[PDB]
Length: 18
Image (cartoon, rainbow, N blue to C red; front, side, top):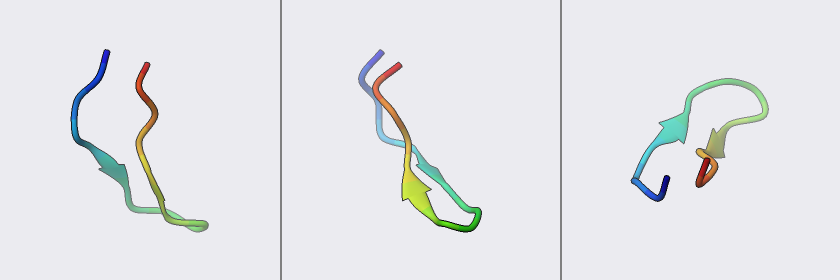
């Protein structure tokens, strides 16, 4: 599902469209 999210981790990465 396409929605705006982002993962705070290392490496830091915007979420995936799943």
